Image (cartoon, rainbow over the protein chains, first blue to last red):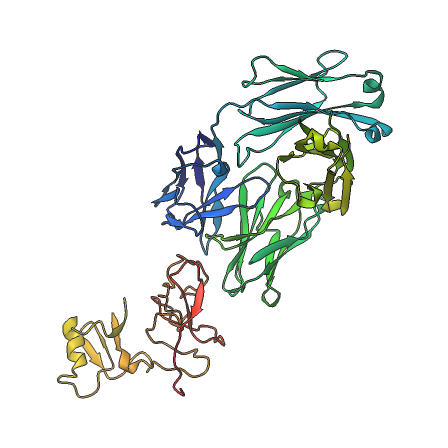
Length: 209
Length: 210
Length: 137
């Protein structure tokens, strides 16, 4: 039909930095192109329409240009809030309307190490047959971390799941929860417990119990 | 305060049919393109169809054309997405949107899940702390998505991390919401998880305690 | 020169318009012309029609208006019907024949109670009713 190829997959920058995103079309479109921003849990926001026309309320740092099959989007002075996914879209009365694959934008940041917590399974969940134990990593950069569970006393693995938040809009950091689930009895016999974290921000990995 | 609000999103069996509705508030119809745009979990946006309120003319995407159809009630400022022969690939959040090429207005979206699994309500367990300290609520073993969590009915937003849910081995979603607060305030101020699971119509408030 | 004062429909010079404007050497009143050659009859009976013989007046709803007014009551310049910018819409001439949707001329293709309106060139205002006097006024 109509193919909108959007490149690259992801781009990174620090505050004040500049980022450029490309959209290229299988057919001509004649300045009928639009740029959208989307943060997780939210609908997209209209940034650019036509190819250059800036929707009201939107900072001038956002720059749209192009024509025929070549389009570009440049965020010039970059704030923490710009961290989102951005999409190129072309829509015409008929036929059709199509989006790009999107492009993820990360904010480069001063390295920050996570604040580590560890949580007890509640009495109530223990009344039931199961027991989950969570380890919390808070506000850290960069995204990459290593978490490993051990207690009484080693390498309990294949039974954990981890979820990671999106990058914060204010401090450009991430956070992550790792959860280890086991039957009641297994954990039940054992008493104290511990989680282990390896991150660029920390000198030697941290164990919280 | 011009709004778009979607409804109808629920859990459906494959091969069945479903009808989503978008209602607009605070503006004339009129005069506009109404498009539906969906987004599968963790994927990109996919436009799927539009209707011109005035024209009555509809256009559908190839991924959808055979089985979906769009209608309107201008008098009631409402658009109907009527879906049939649903497959697993249709599982997504569906957005009612104002426009075709220029989309100034979006709904928050309604989540459609095409599955043979049954609706299960979440169990809420307190994540108890042990200066600044973290505490949480654990929303476990629910299906389908999604679950919204707030703290003290929206009074507490600062430093709150509600994690993206993960599909467990059991086939049920699980999620954690956490918050950093002063340790001193553990005895005095009252912290409650406000958990809402719309697909089950489940609402739970749970006072987390040390 | 005198082409300025003509409702020109393209694809359908100054000497022609001038000699039509003066009615110099004409056995009638020159209501229209093509670029040249003249007529004592317009399309209502490159084409150029005299705005004196284009009724700048309407009845109630004004479904058969065809003037050249292109301003809103707020005084905003109308957006061309060919353009989707700033505002996109389903009002192509192929969907609407004889209703005359060209340039940015005020129009009322569906006999709205508002009378003729236009799409503004202001992005924030999609469409506004053009201020047009009725004959009865």
